Image 1 (cartoon, chains in turn yellow, brown):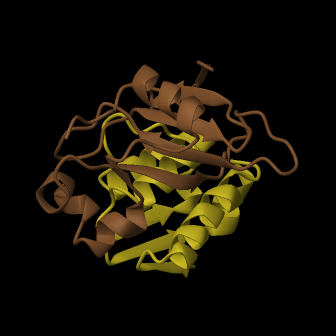
Image 2 (spheres, rainbow over the protein chains, first blue to last red):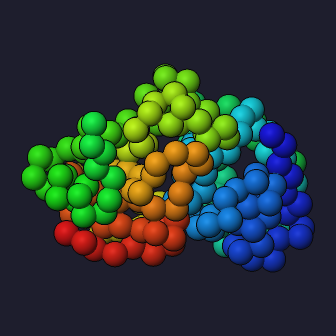
Amino acid sequence: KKAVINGEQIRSISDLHQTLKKELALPEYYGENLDALWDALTGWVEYPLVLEWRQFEQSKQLTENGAESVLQVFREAKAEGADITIILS
Amino acid sequence: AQVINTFDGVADYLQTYHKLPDNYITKSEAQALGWVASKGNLADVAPGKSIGGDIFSNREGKLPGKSGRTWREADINYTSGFRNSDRILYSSDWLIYKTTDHYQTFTKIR
């Protein structure tokens, strides 16, 4: 329903997927990768969903293009029809 | 009406008929029938059905890409309840891969 990401606390691409695993109540088998995220956002997660990504820039640093690629999946899922609200702060 | 949802049964079917078995429906269709993923009610609203056929964007690039080639995926071994971590991956030129660890790793089967 509601998911929060505290950017300043993300040290790796791993921290991010695991933070998402918890914040979105993903399946234990969650693949912790872009494809697994997409499949979870469109065949598992509950809606409506509100994702609040704080300190995005900071988290972008310690993850390379990872954060941006994760954000992209959320954006496409939304364009796909998923009721997702993204708050980039 | 005899469901085909195993890795080999589906692969054989994709290669022999170039389409998924009849027991498959896309996410949009399932939803059109009242499916709600978070409820894990697919079997309730669509008995004997499994999600399959949607375009697969191969976002990690682990599957072999090629201009003109589009990938699609389908659920394998699914019966009822919440979706598992098994998928079959097939290309427009009929290459077949599979994953059992939620898209972490893949194995070419055809």
